[PDB]
Length: 280
Ligand SMILES: Cc1ccc(O)c(C)c1-c1cc(-c2ccnc(N3CCOCC3)c2)cc(C(N)=O)c1N
Image (cartoon, rainbow, N blue to C red):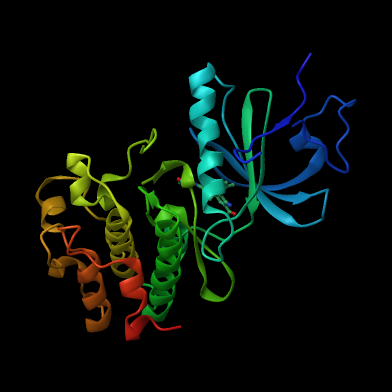
């Protein structure tokens, strides 16, 4: 026999939902959602576009790949939900609707978003810069929100930022969020990593640096180095001309503020948002 689905939350039960019958053998996920498409799959699991039977609206649902192997494995996976709950509701962050576990599998149901910035770039040669400014501003708003909550995203990158309506950006994938102890956290993508993280040092500034390289990459449509001399030369306090062909003086000026190697000299999200060029 199989235990009933249980809600996963770190705030304050078995899952009951209109349309869900525990008497029937299919999973909560099978009974309570219509699977429309698969949006992604990897070792992290699978992500589906679904329609909810409870309210008729569209959502995304992520489910892990294999059953929990032991109590610590379970605890580490469930921690994503606690982190996401700390982020809560914000128009530039992917909103978690509910999470549950059934059959040793973890499900996160969120609002449905569009393609990642990685995907949008790939299927776009370069993005119009007005689009890029929108993505920069919206993800800065997300970072100001995270920092307001004493949170740092240690894996800001094009794959973790999702398009929304009319040019809007939402930051997601909060499994590598840390609170300002740190908690367990996995290896972020070296391409976008702030230099201080090599010495294990982190803070609000690290995700500003990663957003800087994220936006640089999408604006120039060139792969950033994962190590070696080219990695070092993006972390010196200048923009290598290799990456700035086409980029306006205005965008360059803001990126260099974000890419300052000394996290004490690096701009904050709120200071960037207060720049005339990022108004509204
Ligand atoms: C379901 C969910 C739960 C928590 C969460 O934080 C998020 C973002 C999502 C969520 C994830 C994805 C998605 C699609 C394909 N690949 C990835 N990847 C992950 C990072 O590595 C690359 C591959 C992610 C798409 C959407 C969507 N469009 O609505 C979505 N909401």
